[PDB]
């Protein structure tokens, strides 16, 4: 890794220019954790995530021995200055969540591209588990896309090494498995979360929408099993290259990932296979 000076990162981001890139600024994203500014360091654009001290330490401890094509890469950090910073490789295309909703006018993702993104994300989760790590916050917004739209799992601040139980329940409600919501800590929960992500990919719909029926995306699975609604009713209409065969196949994996009984769910390796056999 590599340490950085605070100002160093301040000057690189045009002095923490919180104005969006489309208007001429250096601001890429916000919410929670903090703002992520586009930096220019030696022609090497980076992602300056400015900020809790335990999570700043975890991300760096995890990024330490988990290097893979489908995981964001940690370049450096800044421990000096006021707010703590983290430097990752720059992810041009943002999050899968923002691309599924065509934020700022970006073109809808083709079905073909979505299949590769699902594959890439699964290979990422797989790597994390083979290394006995549990993400705990697998979701659409935590899947970033690079120039070639390669999926990269991000945000390891809540990540854990490894079934145990915790008193401090964390994650995102709309993506959380039953046992996870009760405080259980297990890789089986990442699979469930990924299942919700596969539904986002298929339908282009956000995990939760108050003005909607159902309000939680995960429940459309019951509407489909109760044959009161079909998968075709939910397929994202902002595509024209999605063959019914592989769409149903991805839905099959998604349905399996969303099984209420954590022991009834397939493991990541199985998820990898099915997704692979889906495009084969």
Image (cartoon, rainbow, N blue to C red):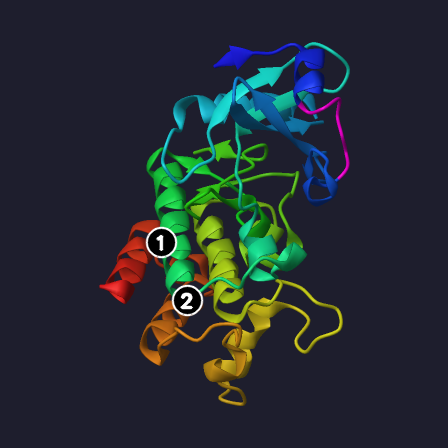
Mark 2 falls on what kind of element?
Answer: helix
Crowdedness near tag 1: few (<14), some (14–19) or many (≥20) residues, C-alpha within 10 Å: many
Q: Mark 2 or mark 1: name the one nearer the start of the chain.
A: 2
Q: Which residues are magenta?
A: 13-19
Residue 253 x/y as whole percent: 37, 65
In this view, which residue lies farthest toward the left?
A: 280
In this view, which residue lies farthest toward the front?
A: 24
Residue 149 x/y as whole percent: 44, 48
Q: Is residue 33 above or below residue 237?
A: above
Can residue 57 be seen here? The reply is yes
Query: Residue drawn 33% across and 38% down?
Result: 130
Helix, strand or loop: magenta stretch: loop
Residue 83 x/y as whole percent: 75, 20
Q: Nearer the viewer, residue 78 or 111?
A: 111
Q: Nearer the viewer, residue 225 or 231?
A: 231
The residue under label 2 is 111
Mark 1 falls on what kind of element?
Answer: helix
Left or right: where does residue 135 sit relative to residue 127? Answer: right
Query: Residue drawn 71% across and 27% down?
Result: 51
Mark 2 vs mark 1, CA separation in Å? 12 Å
Query: Residue drawn 52% across and 84% down?
Result: 233
Left or right: where does residue 157 sit relative to residue 213? Answer: left
Residue 62 x/y as whole percent: 48, 26
Query: Residue drawn 40% across and 59% down?
Result: 113
Q: Nearer the viewer, mark 2 or mark 1?
A: 2
Q: How many circles with numbers are drawn on the protein?
A: 2
Numbered tag placed on residue 119 in the rendering: 1
Can residue 260 be seen here? The reply is no
Numbered tag placed on residue 100 in the rendering: none
User: Is residue 112 magenta-colored?
Assistant: no
């Amino acid at each position: 890794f590599h340490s950085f000076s605070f100002y160093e990162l301040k000057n690189v981001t045009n002095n923490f220019d919180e104005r969006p890139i489309s208007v001429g600024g250096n601001k890429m994203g916000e919410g929670g954790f903090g703002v992520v500014y586009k930096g220019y360091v030696n022609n090497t654009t980076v992602a300056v995530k400015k900020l809790l001290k335990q999570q700043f330490d975890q991300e760096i401890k995890v990024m330490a021995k988990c290097q893979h094509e489908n995981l964001v890469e940690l370049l450096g950090f800044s421990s000096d200055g006021d707010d703590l910073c983290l430097v990752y490789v720059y992810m041009p295309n943002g999050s899968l969540l923002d691309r599924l909703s065509c934020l700022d006018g970006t073109p809808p993702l083709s079905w073909h591209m979505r299949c590769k993104i699902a594959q890439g994300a699964a290979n990422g989760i797989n790597f994390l588990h083979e290394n006995h790590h549990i993400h705990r916050d697998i979701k659409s917004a935590n899947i970033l896309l690079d120039e070639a739209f390669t999926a990269k799992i991000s945000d390891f601040g809540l990540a854990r090494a490894s079934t145990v139980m915790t008193s401090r329940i964390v994650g995102t409600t709309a993506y959380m498995a039953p046992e996870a919501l009760r405080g259980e800590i297990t890789p089986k929960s990442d699979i469930y979360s990924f299942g919700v992500v596969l539904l986002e990919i298929i339908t282009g719909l956000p995990a939760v929408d108050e003005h909607r029926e159902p309000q939680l995306l995960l429940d459309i699975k019951e509407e489909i099993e109760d044959e009161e609604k079909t998968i075709e009713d939910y397929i994202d209409k902002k595509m024209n290259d999605a063959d019914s065969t592989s769409v149903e196949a991805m839905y099959s994996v998604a349905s399996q990932c969303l099984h209420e009984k954590k022991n009834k769910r397939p493991d990541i390796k199985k998820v990898q296979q099915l997704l692979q056999e889906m495009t084969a």
